[PDB]
Image (cartoon, rainbow, N blue to C red; front, side, top):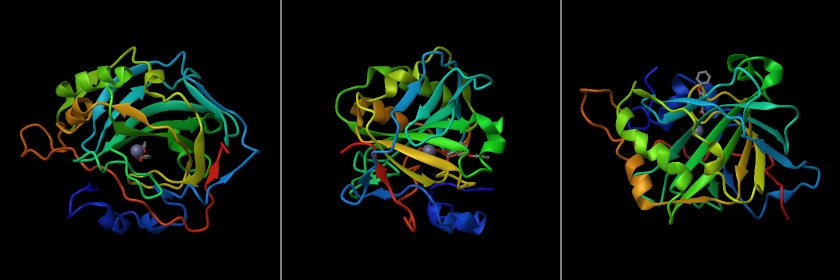
Length: 258
Ligand SMILES: O=C(O)c1cccc(Oc2ccccc2)c1
Ligand SMILES: [Zn+2]
């Protein structure tokens, strides 16, 4: 498969190899704040990242992933809309070429500069590959980034990007604390959806925080110096690696807050 974000291999093309691209629960979506309803039934959200064990950071030619040890319940997401326990496996971002675009989810059609995806899998299914075959297999915590003040807890990420410039490069990335990427409030919207990259599987409970984090222009500029290409190939800057909003179809977005 040779998908990407360009004219010739971008999101409009994905449905030919991945027909679920035109499915009934695709992500991202626009979150219309005047149609999402507060749901008093939602339990409190629980982000338990104290024992998180980061391992490595990888440029996969589409984004970069920070990878965690998920062989036990070290960093887990529970509560909110979720039943049971979801283990953190990795995070990554989507970002733009300019500060006015980059997020995947939008808020009243507003695009943020970037969006962070913290990807977790349901432990009742034993492993990630089994979990993605289930409608409740994953929970992705989505966090918007806006440009303003620097985010200190991001800086160790931006500083390692020089070492994974091109597709296929990885670097050791131990002792990174994903708590430093969270906003103050855990107020969220939730809806059922999908992976936003091929294979676009419809296995995700999305939990999108209302409060963005601020990052500096210098920080996001360094994201934009990555490369989609491999070493010794012509340079294609890793920018605009976001899928646009997909049809909501027969889905309701619920708010955790009034
Ligand atoms: O779009 C994402 O957030 C995402 C996150 C993790 C993995 C992933 O892609 C695969 C999932 C299962 C099998 C092969 C690839 C996509
Ligand atoms: Zn993502």
